[PDB]
Length: 127
Length: 70
Image (cartoon, rainbow over all chains, first blue to last red; front, top):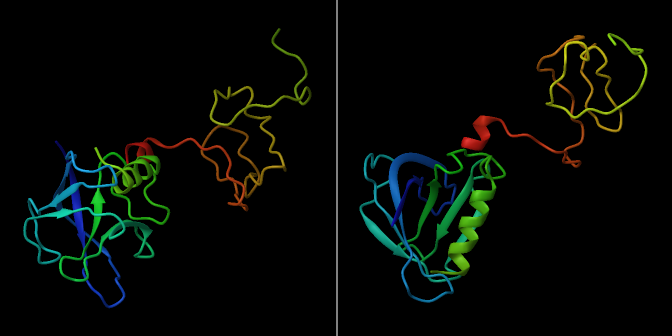
């Protein structure tokens, strides 16, 4: 297994402002052995600091075309990963990878190339 | 020699190489790149702001240690 730090967003359905609220939770990438069309389990739990949005430990699944990556949806902060389940378990997440820093600028982080590889690879294909 | 003929003999030199303090007086800016100093040049080595006026021309770039690590 591989762990990375991950943040929440401010959750709404008003227009989906999705501002990053940085907290200090963690994703846990799990590679599975189902499919090859994209099937990964992203476990978001706030290891520390839950202050930002009311969330509780959860492992959320990847089924294609329902889990979509959008490079900017804040309109001043990139890297918005979006899960849509029709407000049953819709959540927005923004990663706090430390292989490309935590920068919240237009045109992703400064180290772009790490982010471009990782995000496409997980949606389309799976281990 | 100690000498050739300074103020003559053209050749190009890449930015962010070892610029000698005996060749930092003859750094002369070209006009096919937007980059020229906003005011009259120092005559010396250092950080100097060169103006970009087209970001539709992406030019070669050297990341700082900040950008790479982040």
